[PDB]
Image (cartoon, rainbow, N blue to C red; front, side, top):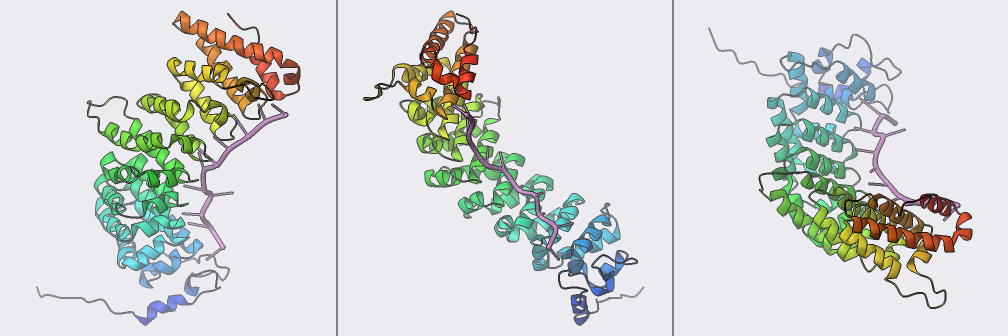
Length: 409
RNA sequence: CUGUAUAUUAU
């Protein structure tokens, strides 16, 4: 037959007729309004496409919910294809809808129903201004659902977009921190090795770690790098983990005695497998010669506890001696570290851990370890009987006396 | 006499 070439009609000014609304809070156009701001009936799905009012419905709560409740799940439906096309025809419209309090949800629903052909277009649009969408409270979600749902090369492309950016700001950010954590917990290590290269700087590692949000980021990074059990002796993550833990090790005194970093240091000590060497170094370098000081602190006390709880005997022995015979008795009060820690609002908890450690280490394979734990527990029991009358007054002293109750050798 | 953190994105 003959060639026919249908060109779309312009419909320029008639788009702005969607600007007129029932109220000023709602952005839903008045042709689709109850008058109470609720979505009208007989609005179908095709009247949205016919009026170019996808954006106006998506910026209204009821409108967007309607789009979500009635979006076609199957990729081969023409209505799904046309609504997706009207979503991604303009990059700026799509990225403003990603940055909308009510629009973000629609993008997410498209991400829930996506195939690879749609995912490529979405990944390009998101990668255009990924860093600022990560900074946004609404888009941050869209970005995280992308990291969950996109194919691994696409999510790799999004992650590597953030390579030479101000990663310190994005990590301490209220919203982009969860994006970085989702990247770390979801994607293979090659997709975010630049993060490990970033936190090899000690200044970047300290600032981010010492932050209400960054702390969990660095922690999530370590957790994932340590969770390797056994590989093919490739020692890759190992080389990367070392690059990170090194700064952690180099500044463990400052990061242990800190509001948020304390948890990371603990995680290390709690980790055991593949981080036991770094646990040992943190105990050796930040904690020993400073146990009485850090057990009197609000934050570092927990570190001293997790240490006494997970430390190996070879180190526990040193920790115990430092407390029992490591400090010079106070000039005026003639008080030992235990004496000071026994009646401390925080130190009491440490002594209790020390008692636990000694009780659990009596059931050890080595009889000499059992003898040394029994001796340490005897030293604790001796100071507690010396101070028992004052210890009955306290809840902690009741716990301590109950802990040393009917004990073995 | 008890001690620390981790978005409730829907005007």
